[PDB]
Amino acid sequence: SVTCPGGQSTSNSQCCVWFDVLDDLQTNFYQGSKCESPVRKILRIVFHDAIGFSPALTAAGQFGGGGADGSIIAHSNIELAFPANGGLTDTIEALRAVGINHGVSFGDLIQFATAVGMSNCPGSPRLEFLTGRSNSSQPSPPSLIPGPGNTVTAILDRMGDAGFSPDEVVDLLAAHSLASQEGLNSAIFRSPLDSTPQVFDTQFYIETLLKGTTQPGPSLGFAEELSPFPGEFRMRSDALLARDSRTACRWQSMTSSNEVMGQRYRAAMAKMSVLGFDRNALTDCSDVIPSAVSNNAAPVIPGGLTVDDIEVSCPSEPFPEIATASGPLPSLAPAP
Ligand code: HEM
Ligand SMILES: *[C@@H]1O[C@H](CO)[C@@H](O[C@@H]2O[C@H](CO)[C@@H](O)[C@H](O)[C@H]2NC(C)=O)[C@H](O)[C@H]1NC(C)=O
Ligand SMILES: [C-]#N
Ligand SMILES: [Ca+2]
Ligand SMILES: [Ca+2]
């Protein structure tokens, strides 16, 4: 049966090359299978590559973007000049070299490096991995990536055009559970967006709902809001989507179960991975993706804050009963 050169069993012979790029990425790109900045930069890249897809531009007779086509690498010279693509150059060049060296398409490589990077982070689901996306791409049109200063209406229209419902936009944002910022407020470089930047969990949904109390840095950066405790950064779009009536009930439902969040995120990522492609024309190589270590911690409201400190915004559903922690308010270290 298809046994690959290294002796692993896979579904199709097209999956065998991916065991070599697995080894390369884990040893080199990810510095020994770690869940640090390279994983977080690849999650920004997979989103920025895939979202350059617009049915509305196509309808108006313009090129609407090829979706998850690897154009952010093949055409980095034009796409990294876009406002939302700062701080990605070094990661793009590292991925370029792996793609050229292994002979795999850039669009497939980005989806693969996302599933492999997430497997290094405790609590992650096993993402689907399909191979076969053409290596040819045209540059993404500008203005298709949502920005942190955009209103909720602007973000939902952009994401809706690409094909996501308001619920799926909230589901996709679970990736901010493994996040920090570097370019919005450089004075507090790598300030985390939740208290566990290395654990794929529910904390990001809980903590964005908390009352904004603290200014973490010397001044406020672009699209920065007050956060709940020292060291945590809060961006305006996340604060607004947590409280807006169109997204608030889904945001609240994401707070108490890591299992539900992981399933919803996996489904939304599988949809995003094939924007611009027919998934029935691709080959499934999901069995090449390893399991992540399980997260055994329960959701908690950190540092002595209680349910009275969260700004409940879903008028129909009572806030879930989440555990509290007896403690002084945390001060977060920079994400690694
Ligand atoms: C509603 C749209 C979203 C907006 C407006 C948004 C905006 C941003 C911004 C401004 C940053 C900080 C980047 C920096 O200064 O270094 C950030 C970080 C991040 N975002 Fe998003 N994001 C959104 C959705 C997503 C999605 C859907 C994903 C991917 C599945 C994603 C993954 C990440 C990750 C992992 C980071 C952390 C990067 C790092 O630590 O270096 N974001 N996002
Ligand atoms: C995918 O297409 C890109 C071109 O867009 C190819 O990238 C070039 O590859 C050659 C050698 O193979 C390098 O010297 C160039 O510097 C690369 N250019 C860019 C923009 O990266 C790539 O080889 C193609 N990959 C496959 C498997 O066909
Ligand atoms: C996130 N961009
Ligand atoms: Ca693209
Ligand atoms: Ca987290």
Image: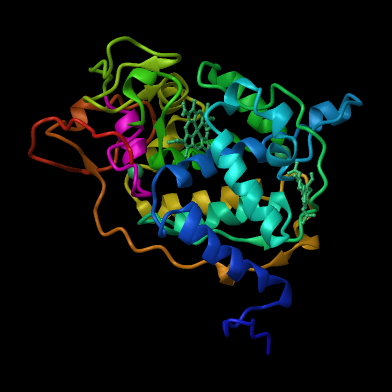
Q: Hey, which residue is sitting farthest top in the picture?
A: 219
Q: Hey, which residue is sitting farthest right in the picture?
A: 61
Q: Residue at x 71, y 77 (%)?
A: 12
The image shows residue 242, relative to residue 281, as above or below, that is above
**In-image side of 253 versus 130 (left or right):** left
Q: Quadrant of the C terminus?
A: top left
Residue 212 in the image: state x and y as whole percent: 28, 19
**In-image side of 168 versus 296 (left or right):** right
Residue 177 in the image: state x and y as whole percent: 39, 41
Which of 335/225 is in front?
335
Looking at the rendered structure, the number of numbered marks drawn on it comes to 0
- The answer to whether residue 133 is magenta is no
Q: Is residue 263 visible?
A: no
**In-image side of 266 versus 300 (left or right):** right
Q: Is residue 72 visible?
A: yes
Q: Quadrant of the N terminus?
A: bottom right
Please report the bounds of the magenta region as a residue range: 192-210
The image shows residue 60, relative to residue 115, as above or below, that is above
Q: Residue at x 66, y 39 (%)?
A: 49
Residue 103 in the image: state x and y as whole percent: 73, 60
Q: Residue at x 31, y 41 (%)?
A: 203
Quadrant in the picture for residue 105: bottom right
Quadrant in the picture for residue 59: top right
Residue 290 in the image: state x and y as whole percent: 48, 68
Quadrant in the picture for residue 235: top left
